[PDB]
Image 1 (cartoon, rainbow over the protein chains, first blue to last red):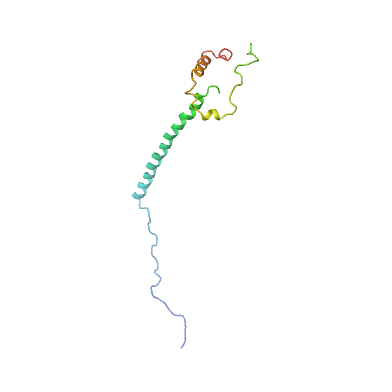
Image 2 (cartoon, rainbow over the protein chains, first blue to last red):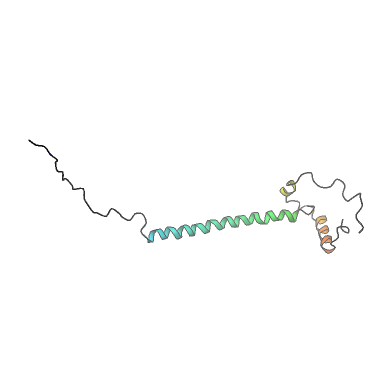
Length: 69
Length: 52
């Protein structure tokens, strides 16, 4: 018997198929997070600015209180 | 020009260290009557020689 190269089929590798698929973000869903992060962003930032006003008047008060300076 | 006397005003003047004054803002509330009258004198008459 003579032995040569043998053939293999099984699944035939599956040639030409789109492996690319959309993931995580769809379109409308990411905009709700996007503007949602903005709405949370400005609201939390301005609370510290109002807290800065408590310091702002009190810091400049030191110059008014000190006249022997 | 007529300058002030060599003896100067207020014997043993000013505190020894700074920031100490800035730490206490209670100096605005207590003892304000001598402070404000000096302030009223200085804006009306700009000369330091008059309101010393």
